[PDB]
Length: 257
Length: 257
Ligand SMILES: O=c1[nH]c(=O)n([C@@H]2O[C@H](COP(=O)(O)O)[C@@H](O)[C@H]2O)c(=O)[nH]1
Ligand SMILES: O=c1[nH]c(=O)n([C@@H]2O[C@H](COP(=O)(O)O)[C@@H](O)[C@H]2O)c(=O)[nH]1
Ligand code: PRO
Ligand code: PRO
Image 1: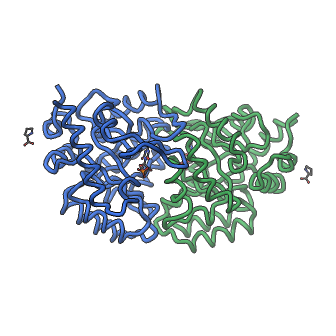
Image 2: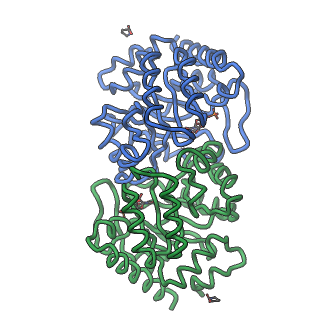
Image 3: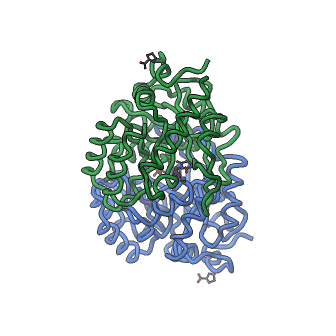
């Protein structure tokens, strides 16, 4: 009954950003999102260029780049177009709608001008989505809602997660999916992206907890693994990305049957 | 039984940032925080200079400033020192500890270098605090935890709010208080700052809901009102700030008896 990524890309209610993502995931045999958690633009762009072919998405934290400029994002877009991946700015909007509108469009970062995807916490209520949508819908962007978190003590559980899902299913013109640790929506037009991923067991010293690609894609039913340190701390980041890609892709294939 | 701000500033377990804030609130007879939600540095600095004497705190969203530079924050610090108010960067950190550490210290904004106070959502678990504290404690900064929000559909209620309070009471070396709509902690060393404040009833079109200074300081027991549009959209921002200051200050005095 599970549809392939390529088939999900054609669903009637699919958002165009999700459809583009699903089509390139199927074409490239990748459901890996690189979390490019680096402070130097040159390293961001060298990673994007070398690992571009292995990834479906590159997740940025632009407010940790020491040398951010809009020109850096222009170069990143050139690579995303060349290698075919989407740019996800992991900004975690989490304010009232009137504020996030300006945070998304304006300031130094002009996030909406270069990010295909952004994410938002649902704790403020649906005004967070409505505010972002006022900017993002005209710019043909999409939003991910944070339905679960991977860190110890996360409060994004139970009824909070269910509120996130309902908020997404009510704003499907702009919300394309979730950050979660598992499948949280039964609707196949919604993407599920899962961080806290490493091939080995463990965590970090600040509350991160890791699960494997096979677990999060296979058993828990998510679509895309978001990997940072498991790739970016490795000596050979390209081979590491390929290891994560093959893991997440096989897990997806085995789930479909 | 309620202690004055000046007395709370001397409590044994008071954090130095809170003590400094409480002492200047008492000296200046102001418990008003200006939410300086503007896009131009010149307007930010003209507001800070003119309204400085009327406020205990200026809350920034630096990621909406079109013309942010570190020099703008240097000029803002000069005014905060001159007029005696604290600078609160309303960044709403809301990520895993390892990420927020870098978001706080680094990037273009170097928030920890100029903000006396920042705030954090508790949804990631206590790693968000631990990560920020790794930067902020050495820099003698403080953090506010978001225990409630003013916007329609807020999920920061019930057990979520109680988790925020517990997280604050367990990280009192760095957490100085809360963003909330009411008193949520019975411990007087913790500040309570309340946004969603206007003299008239109403809201905005993106989910903001307003309550009056008398209600939030008087009946609901909060310490400081955070006001944006009720001041910044008025023609005479100084007279508006004075109106809000007198409202919040009288409400506090009447509560003490
Ligand atoms: O629940 C969540 N957990 C999580 O780690 N992230 C983010 O995803 C990345 C994980 O990085 P690594 O731990 O793999 O090195 C970091 O950039 C976090 O900010 C996230 O967005 N949501
Ligand atoms: O619950 C919350 N509600 C809230 O409005 N704020 C913030 O406080 C300010 C309110 O602005 P006004 O509605 O008064 O013009 C804006 O800068 C919001 O981002 C906040 O931080 N928390
Ligand atoms: O991607 C493709 O080519 C096919 C078309 C139908 C679904 N998948
Ligand atoms: O601020 C003051 O001067 C007094 C001293 C004790 C408490 N308040």
